[PDB]
Image 1: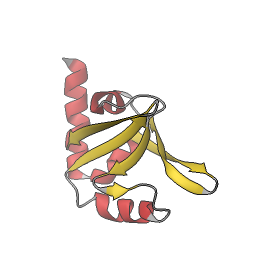
Image 2: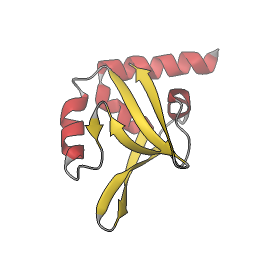
Image 3: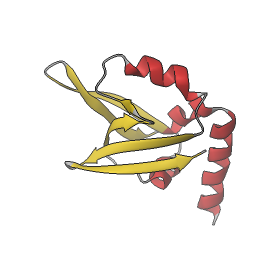
Image 4: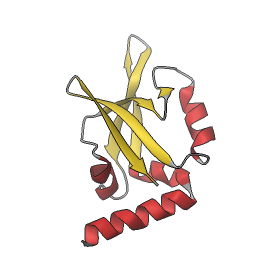
Length: 105
């Protein structure tokens, strides 16, 4: 009950300031031969949000709100655009299997 309420209070703050999502969901580039495969996703300031979205440790994001995360320049665009979005749809590869996960702010 209290974790759900805490997750709702984080979401509300993200809704008001979407870049705050990056305090909770950390992305770190994965490369193979100098090509970016995507971003390893890990929990940030309070892991409850990362957990609530359906993310697990070791997941690699390959698409985010329709942005192809193999594009070496796309992070520029992601950050420029985040404050304009009201959800995050993520496609992650998890032990070699893709999953779509979702949070509406």
